[PDB]
Image 1: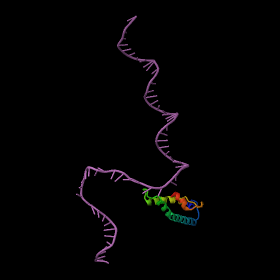
Image 2 (image 1 turned 90 degrees about the vertical axis):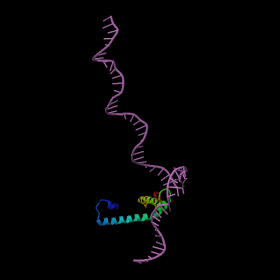
Image 3 (image 1 turned 180 degrees about the vertical axis):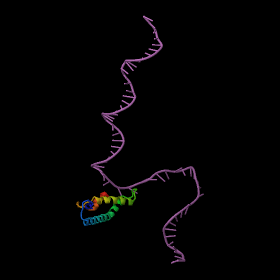
Image 4 (image 1 turned 120 degrees about the vertical axis):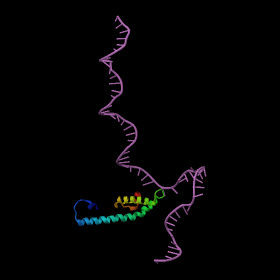
Length: 88
DNA sequence: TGCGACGGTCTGACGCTCTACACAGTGCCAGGGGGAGATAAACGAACGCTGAACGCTCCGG
C-alpha cells in the first residue's frame, strides 16, 4: 500500500496486485485484532469497578491495542502479548 | 384462526411538617509545548525647575 501510494507510474496489473496484497494485509490487521480481543478483555476486567464501565474500558483498551499493532515488529523475537500489555 | 395461558410490561400504591445524613478494596517516568509569574529597557508624556517678566500698590526720599 505504500508503493501504490507513491505517484510513480507502474503497471496497472502490478497496482492491482499491490492492492490485493494491501487487502490481505488489512485482513491480517483484523485477524490479529480479533485474536487479541480476549487479552484486552482480560486486562480491562483487571481495571474494572472504579467508576468507569466495563465495556468502555474494553473499547479504550482496544484503541490501545490497535496502537500496539501499529507499533509492533517481528524483528524482535518476542510474543505479541508481552508487548501489547504495556499499551493496554 | 380460535383458544387460554404464558408472559412481559406498566402503572400507582391519601396528605402535610416536627423531624432531615451520610456515603468505603489493585503502575511509572521521560521528553516536549504554553503560560503563569519576574526582569530591565523603551518611546512618549507631563511633570518640575529655571526665576524671568508684567503689573500692581506701595512707603517714600
